[PDB]
Image (tube, rainbow, N blue to C red; front, side, top):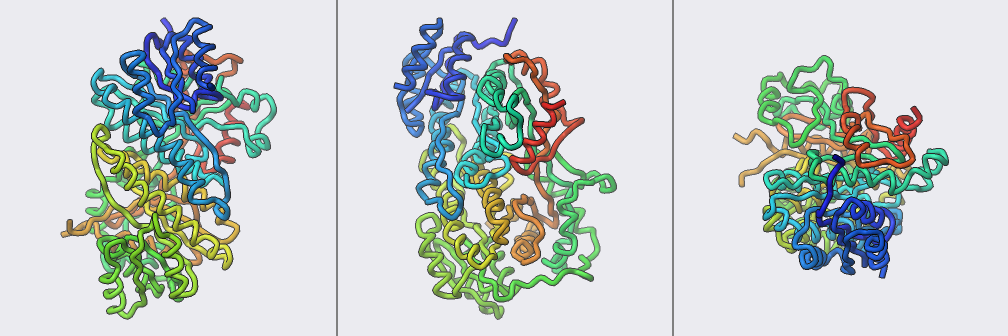
Length: 582
């Protein structure tokens, strides 16, 4: 018998047209009870369904009102089993033009609407011990994309959100996945021939969406590229990495000496604890630091000079803890450091100056006052060269009990604040054709982590944001890199901030040879993090079914051969052309 959906209640946000409308029709054809949500338009879809023998009701709500949407499903059908997070909206602009409101609007619909709807769906999933969630990402979420700083931030966030829901959801038989469907754009239309472009639509996406939405599906926490008959799983590949002895000899200059080793994925000759991994959580730091501590002293002989002399560094959340130490490293390498902190920047400043360094306080809130922070920097030192967006809070909670306040405040500090500050630094960087942005992500954002749906989603927002800003920055010599440290403070220490800071100051130099890159780091260890995309399956039929996904799953999830490591939407699209081309 075929893949079954009978009597499954299915909420699809933004279902008045495009992908969302198609899914509504396909689901209902297979006997599902669809809640068609669209902010008239929903009615049009609900009429086709009923006319053609199906069950559907309309919901007119804003996706922020996720409680009311699910309330619609419950009234009409007694529960919900599937959420398809589809609702969207575009406000494209380069980093030069994009406003704060353009940014928050796109985060709201894509990310905060998903939180609202899913949060509301969650009790019902828990009680019946069943749920199926599909988060709509996009290639711009995976890779960054020019002019879409927001949209990439939201679509990338939804990766980490999906991983977190998959981890929290497992015991309740709730599985969560993300898709990244390639769209017709100017880029695609210049890479792909007319026959593939006309298959680049909902009919070729929906089969995987249905499959991932079914009881038969066992896959969870996973991402997939989908386009014109192609379907392939795409996962994280983290390099074997390098170990440094975690002592005074672990300097910024040794990193620079051995930098290329970090991004080197040939792990043939390395031992087992430093082979490439395909991870689902942070690295085995206990093994790593244990091995790093057996090493002889880091040799800095032949190392590149590292100096941040007369560079102005702005670092946020640096009044205490890890950030405080990071700053002291930036200052000891010669930078004039504006130390931002919401509570107190004084103690970091005093300590910096007691060591013969130059620093200056700022105590504005990042999200709220990015303008006042940039003015503060310029008033004092006349310019800005390096931005390290480190500000943070933690509001940990199971997803079932996470409140909206806990969701937003985390989001405001980590994601919004990083953008708003970055946006106001930006014109200075481009004017002088120099900028070095160092954004702090997290293994909780990259791999997801139960109890941290907010922290993880936001820090995963950072990947998309950073990557975009790296694309746009390249021509004006503005490099932006991403870092997921493992380090603790006091509240011996094998994971000091001293084991992370060296990388951070190197990322600030003139001669840092990469941009858009992701690093995980701690305990004497440094690694890089990238994509590996599977062989994939190709449907050649002009109608593709959910059955095709079922029968060719082996090929979709096959990392044994013909894999790819795309790092831009252009790279992915060329590779998809090649697999479909045969």
